[PDB]
Amino acid sequence: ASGRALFQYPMTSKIELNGEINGKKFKVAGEGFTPSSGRFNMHAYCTTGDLPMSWVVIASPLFHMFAHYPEDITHFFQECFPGSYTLDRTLRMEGDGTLTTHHEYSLEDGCVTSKTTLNASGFDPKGATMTKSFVKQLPCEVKITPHGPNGIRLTSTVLYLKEDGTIQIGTQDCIVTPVGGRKVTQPKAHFLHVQIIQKKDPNDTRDHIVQTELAVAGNLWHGMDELYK
Ligand SMILES: [Cl-]
Ligand SMILES: [Cl-]
Image 1 (cartoon, rainbow, N blue to C red):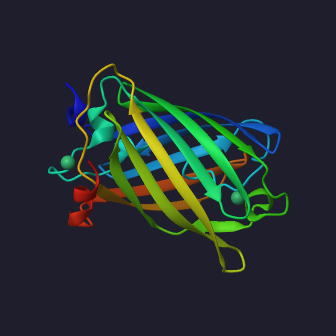
Image 2 (cartoon, rainbow, N blue to C red):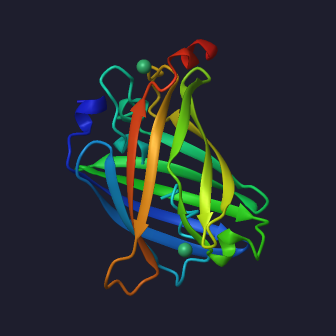
């Protein structure tokens, strides 16, 4: 049993995330549900006190293996199992700061655990990330291409909405590397539509978020694949 046969729904998730931003160290944990292909939630909480940054900016750090793929695009993230992959991200909040994250994953008993680290240095202390002035990030199209002999790369430019109704841009790039000691067949160039919605739990006493992601792959520009050898 490998690849897509390992991703029979429903499934669940866990996260452990160790972070630091501008010298403030913090931890997040969470549990989540994946009811069906491409719809996945995560109820996360800060275990060290209040989260020292926007929940909206930490959203993308908070599981591409749950994306919904049609049959005729390789689901690279799922095809990495067994063996797993790492994800290394850079998120440049333009005029504000840059963060990186590193993610390792394991699958057991229908549950994907993410163990993530986040490092962020040089953020503007009065910017929207540190003062928590963001409301949401708008849905994006993530460009996915083959990268090196055995990886993929993901890129997006994301609009973050502030409380005053104006926008800040994040520029984001990820590299996915199989760690399972084997070759995984790369997909053709394609795109992932990503929508992230956040709400609070009516009762939870912790600093937390209840997040849902919809992620759907599609060959949005058929000609793109020609450009990536
Ligand atoms: Cl927030
Ligand atoms: Cl493909």
